[PDB]
Length: 14
Length: 414
Image 1 (cartoon, rainbow over the protein chains, first blue to last red):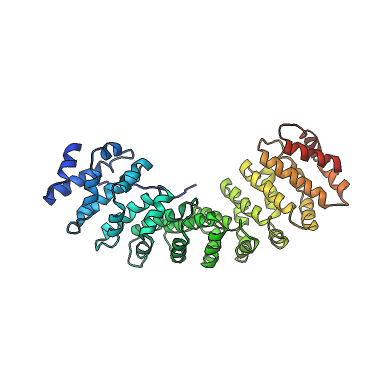
Image 2: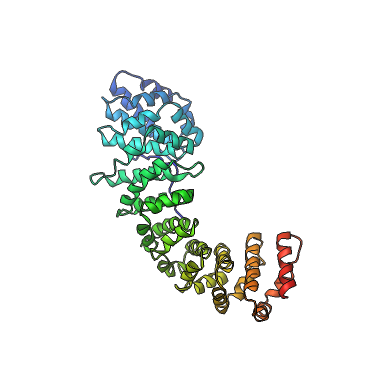
């Protein structure tokens, strides 16, 4: 089970 | 603080302005539950929108789209605000920026917007996002970029009601035919899941997949090393065999059945359920396709899961034995019986899923209606295996559709 995500955030580190 | 950031973002000095949007991005990329609501109410949105127009300052465009992307990654109410601040045409304009860090972050923002709804999907499509997006697929593109491109190509296919236009589907498939041969794991998975949704729309789009000629490259993925790839491929090909018999044959003409002995015996029950569900639709076609399930030595493996499998696998397995019962010839149903299909097939009436109960009994009905002479012979098998006792007690009023069936079966053969 690994359906692709609908929405995505771009995380920083930095 | 918050009020200072929304003020410093309007400065004419690029130094203070840039270092203020960089702060607005971190507050959205510092955890997994950012203060997005307080950010929208802070009035930062129109300033982030206008920052997208500063062709003279690329680093401001990058940080601005990043901030807007993460706001779109939230709830629908959070994503609507980014599209309600007139930011979609500026993103599309950024798809042609000479700064790859700006082109990528604009793609990322559009995918979240496309993923919210089919309305927002057809909106960005009508403006023309497909033609520049698919122009990124090239050798010299980084892999981290292509992964974002394929994922937006998934949301461009994701919704089926209403389904995406044919003009866009006809433009995507020649790119999937190029992305299906990639070596990266995540790209191939996304390339096949997009095919799953295109095959989930309807028979009109399934033929577009067929006419594109990508099915010969989709079937071998049933035996790919990565289970993530088969699971999408098993779903993608699994939807194709739900339309016309002439479309299901194109699947079988690619030697699809020769990949199932590794799936019907797979340890993961989700694959087992998804595998028999494929064979169920195959047993619904004509007799030649039904015989193909027989010429592959798959029927005993279907029955074994019908006997010792899980509930979700048995439900699709009882369906698999049923569609074959009302479609195939007499020797094909007779072949089922000599494969000892009688004991486990009747041991599923005690389930509380009325659909399965209807399925078996209808299949139990059509079996006895086909073997005209062997009525007493097969009846002894059902009575000895303990089915008739369960058939007798199925004459209860908790479902008239079952009561009517369990009586006629008794009244004609028992």
